[PDB]
Image (cartoon, rainbow, N blue to C red; front, side, top):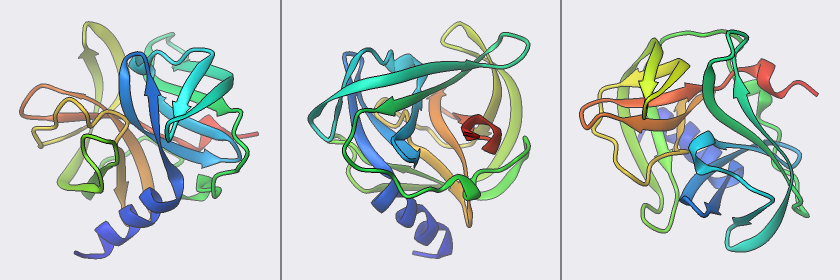
Length: 182
């Protein structure tokens, strides 16, 4: 509808895949080469389904901060025959608050879904499903089962992936440029 949705659509159309694990179907953001991200609660194993293709996982790392606190981001390298468009220059360098964000989802359940979530707070600490978690972004939207892995963007920045909610608010794990240095 506007330039917010334009940037979100551009990311969804080239940098997402449908990832299926034993814990369900997730939106999965491809960042560069064969490297993607997914919420750690997806429980990635040795084999994952990517757009319903059986795919070997070459490496998976559940990220934690230097306090050894969960970040709820898993970085996956896929044995895929094709690279992602490199979007690392759209990742923020530092923890921040944002205005006027979009949460975008693409699964079997929720195809081509875009949500204007409004103001994003640097919330910090969240007890997420009983797991102490850091670097949480918060937005005021009643997100649902099926939106985890959803991409949070502003015009020109990919800032997070959706990892939970409490019925009134939604929560995203920050993406930072420093996670994907090679």
